[PDB]
Amino acid sequence: DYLLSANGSKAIDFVWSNFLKHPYNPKLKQPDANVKAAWEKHADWEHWSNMGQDWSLNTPSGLVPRPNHGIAHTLRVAQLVPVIAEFLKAYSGDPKFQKLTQKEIQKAQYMMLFSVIGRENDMSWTDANHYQQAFKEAYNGQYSKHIYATFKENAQKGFLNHVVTNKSSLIPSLFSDESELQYWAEALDTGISSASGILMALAHDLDLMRCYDKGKFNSLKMKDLVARLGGNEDAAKKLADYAHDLIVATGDRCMGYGVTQDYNYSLFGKCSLDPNECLKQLQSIPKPETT
């Protein structure tokens, strides 16, 4: 809905041109030797190479930077938000989800456009916890700034930059005033009980089927989604099927759910190098109906 609006289109162009079309930062590709050694002692941690994973992807259309957190991912999580809201209203059994007016849902969708702009590598929140702990263990307890939290602070900076540059178009029609804007900017700091926060978290969670294996996606994402939909596994599966179909529509990899696939390099390149083409492919997917 909001992604074709003037405000949506301008936000997409901002995040694409200033952040998402550019490479990750080579200085964040891997830890130093000391941090690596401390990290490797934790056999239960995913390997430190997660920091440099998914750096870029060659496609017939060009070399795609940040392929696992680029324009296709960003547009999909934004597109998921209104559909998730309709599923929550239909199946959650929690009346708190009717605080989701169109304006609320549009703000949540808008925020998702800024949800990965601060990234300088592909590492997860858990990876950043591990880096910070490994740093402490390698360097006599010394403190280091949490890498993922720094990404989110940089995203807040870029979000606020865009919104204030376009304040007359966004306040009060999307954000009522500067105080409300401040609350939504603080909502980018994702590490959650509000209706809009749950909505944004579920969009992030669903799209992780692109990079989680099936055991991890089912245990860490699907169980929670089913419980949020009142235990309705059929409804959760319809919603996950939609997230899967958006992934396939953009040529992206799908590892954790449904009919799995590797990248379609041609389609992924076309979508990942042209936001408007990516959005066109996304909107060709039927939105599921709720009872």
Image: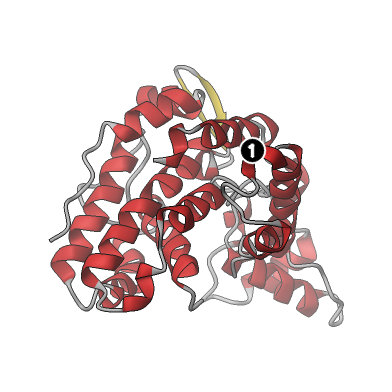
Circle 1 SS class: helix
For the residue carrying disc 1, how many other residues have a C-alpha within 10 Å: few (<14), some (14-19), or many (20+)?
A: some
Q: Which residue: 34% across, 64% down?
A: 217
Q: Residue 7, image x and y in percent?
A: 56, 36
| Residue type at numbered disc 1 | Ser
| Percent coordinates x, y for residue 126 in the rendering | 58, 69
Q: Quadrant of the C terminus?
A: bottom left
Residue depicted at 47% across the width and 61% down the height:
200
The answer to whether one can see residue 268 in this image is: no
Decide which of 21, 262 is in the foreground and name it. Answer: 21
Name the residue located 57 percent from the left edge and 39 percent from the top edge.
66
Q: Is 121 above or below relative to 277? A: below
Say which of 18 and 266 sits in front.
18
Q: Is residue 51 above or below residue 232?
A: above
Task: Name the residue that disc number 1 marks.
Answer: 169
Q: Which residue does the image show at 28% across and 66% down from the upper left?
A: 89
Residue 78 horizontal/vertical position (percent):
45, 47
Front residue (pair 84, 247): 84
Nearer-the-camera pick, 8 or 146: 8
Q: Is residue 65 left or right of residue 79?
A: right
- Vertical comparison of 8 with 158: above or below: above
